[PDB]
Amino acid sequence: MDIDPYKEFGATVELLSFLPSDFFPSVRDLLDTAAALYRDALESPEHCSPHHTALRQAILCWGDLMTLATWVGTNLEDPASRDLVVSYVNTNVGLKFRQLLWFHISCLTFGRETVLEYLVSFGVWIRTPPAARPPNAPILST
Amino acid sequence: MDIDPYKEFGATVELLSFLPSDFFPSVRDLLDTAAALYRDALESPEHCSPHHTALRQAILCWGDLMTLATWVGTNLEDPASRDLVVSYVNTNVGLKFRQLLWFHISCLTFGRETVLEYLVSFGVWIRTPPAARPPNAPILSTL
């Protein structure tokens, strides 16, 4: 069974690894932003949007991963060395959520296509050597 | 940030724990049920329903979870400590996803309210004294 988290939103995992791995904020920063910009819709009893639905599942999923990695770090080894279980999650999967978290928060703010366009525009822009690219990078707004 | 997976769907975490711990299939059974019944709608570029989108995340999330919980099985040694993660997985989250997976597969199959009513009814039935309850439990079948 093969599911692209983005296919239903008009994008893919190809399109997101299209941006450099350091382009995205941290997972901790992206969650802080979710609360700060949307908590009431996110805690609301309404669907609101497919982006809202997806965002809530993605926030909570990182919750299911972190909770599991912390309870499993505590039960054999030192709280100073047990951060290999939480280290592990930020190496394999931590990058994946960084893309996914950002993608939806961004889509809520500016509009799905805006973010889609922004990804292709900013993507070809970052690859372009300094001398060949405009001084004004693509910008993300309404 | 404090979010109920079910609130937007007319349910709550209280409401699903209304049901016994053993009533739900394994996760492994639920995903194979899902694959076999829905692979094509779930793999579609279409939302279909809020249930579909929430489901896709959850199926995919269980993928990310097993990847983590198995990697710590690799880093273990004791025959009682390797079995420390799949003790938790069968207790804390495996139960959570079993409910969540089940809630959604079912809603797609039978209808949101259908699945909801069934939860109250089966819930009150299991709580109901044997001798006071009908022999025939509330039923989950194709409307």
Image: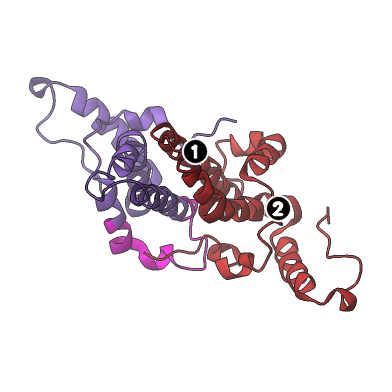
Chain colours: A purple, B red
Chain to which the residue tagged by mark 1 belongs: B
What SS does tag 1 mark? loop
The residue wearing badge 2 is B106
The stretch in magenta equals: A32-54
Residue at 39% x, 27% y is A14
Where is the C terminus of chain B found, in terms of image quarters? bottom right
Residue at 44% x, 38% y is B78
Taking B96 as reference, is A13 left or right? left
Question: Mainly helix, strand or loop, the magenta region?
Answer: helix
Chain to which the residue tagged by mark 2 belongs: B
User: Can residue A94 be seen at all in this image of the molecule?
Assistant: yes
- The answer to whether residue A81 is above or below residue B110 is above
Residue at 52% x, 44% y is B86
Q: Nearer the viewer, residue B4 or B22?
A: B22
Taking A74 as reference, is B112 left or right? right
Residue at 47% x, 39% y is B82
Which percent across, then down, holds residue A52? 45, 55
Taking A131 as reference, is B59 left or right? right
Farthest right residue?
Answer: B135
- The answer to whether residue B101 is above or below residue B72 is below
C-alpha gap between disc 1 and disc 2: 37 Å
- The answer to whether residue A85 is above or below residue A13 is below
Q: Nearer the viewer, residue A116 or B21?
A: B21
Amino acid type of disc 1?
Pro
Q: Is residue A34 magenta?
A: yes
Amino acid type of disc 2?
Ser
